[PDB]
Amino acid sequence: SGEYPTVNEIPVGEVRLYQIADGVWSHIATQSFDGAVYPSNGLIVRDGDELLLIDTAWGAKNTAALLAEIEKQIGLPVTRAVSTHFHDDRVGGVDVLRAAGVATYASPSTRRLAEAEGNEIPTHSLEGLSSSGDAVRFGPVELFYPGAAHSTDNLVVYVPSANVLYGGCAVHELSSTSAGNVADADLAEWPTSVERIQKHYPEAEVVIPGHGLPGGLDLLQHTANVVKAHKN
Ligand SMILES: C[C@@H](c1cccc2c(-c3cnn(C)c3)c(C(=O)O)[nH]c12)N1C[C@]2(C[C@@H](CN)C2)OC1=O
Ligand SMILES: [Zn+2]
Ligand SMILES: [Zn+2]
């Protein structure tokens, strides 16, 4: 009923959209992993009479449900998708997307890691993102590689028309008490990577984490704080 949808509010298999700004939505889905249920976010950005998708909905069936929810709520075709790192909450569902006419993209680093680990593999490589601080345009967004954080390949996405910063899993929600799933993280570099984001996007108005509630710029400092304390 208008609040940001939360883990116990979304059954696994269902997807909800949330309007962030004009032409910008997040998508929210839930999934089971190692016997616990988690929410996760992605992004939808209007690209003329088409849509750009950022990240899958964490699984094939969730991603099919995402496409159906987009058709119901927005009614414009998803033509391209970008996955912001190699984990299943970002690429699981890429095969569904490809079979539904969506061209799927990720950095070469993400594609290599997905392949090596047995995750679904985006079709197209995004060059120009291999060095921290790199940025490239992709339709209505800018893609930025901040350096290693949650993963070595994590990308962030900025929507300049709306000053929306989608941090993906390199950015944690304000209620977070831990650095999330750190299996593939670089806790030592993470605060430096967040500092790069802060420097590059000082006018961000909305910051969206990979999991949990959007907020403002304070999500970036909070993330640095909880990663440093985790490492400690
Ligand atoms: C799919 C994703 C994942 C699974 C379950 C929980 C989380 C969370 C999370 C947990 N708590 N909160 C608040 C968020 C985050 C996050 O932090 O992005 N990702 C998660 N995987 C799995 C993996 C690959 C490794 C294989 N050995 C383990 O690593 C990840 O990230
Ligand atoms: Zn991850
Ligand atoms: Zn994640």
Image: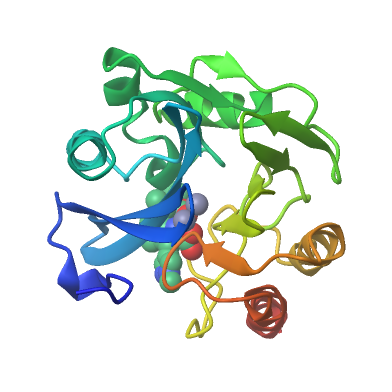
Q: Is residue 51 left or right of residue 107?
A: left
Q: Is residue 84 left or right of residue 190?
A: left
- Residue 50 at x, y = what percent? 43, 26
Front one among 163 and 36: 163
Q: In this view, does 74 lie above or below 108?
A: below
Name the quarter showing ligand 1.
bottom left
Front one among 108 and 185: 108
Task: Tell me the quarter of the image containing the C terminus.
Answer: bottom right
Which residue: 30% across, 77% down?
Answer: 3
Q: In which quarter of the image is residue 99?
A: top left
Which residue: 61% across, 36% down?
Answer: 140
- Residue 151 at x, y = what percent? 62, 50
Q: Is residue 125 left or right of residue 190?
A: left
Q: Is residue 60 visible?
A: no
Q: In which quarter of the image is residue 44?
A: top left
Which residue: 39% across, 26% down?
Answer: 120
Front one among 82 and 76: 76
Q: Quadrant of residue 172?
A: bottom right
Q: In this view, does 123 lie above or below 146?
A: above
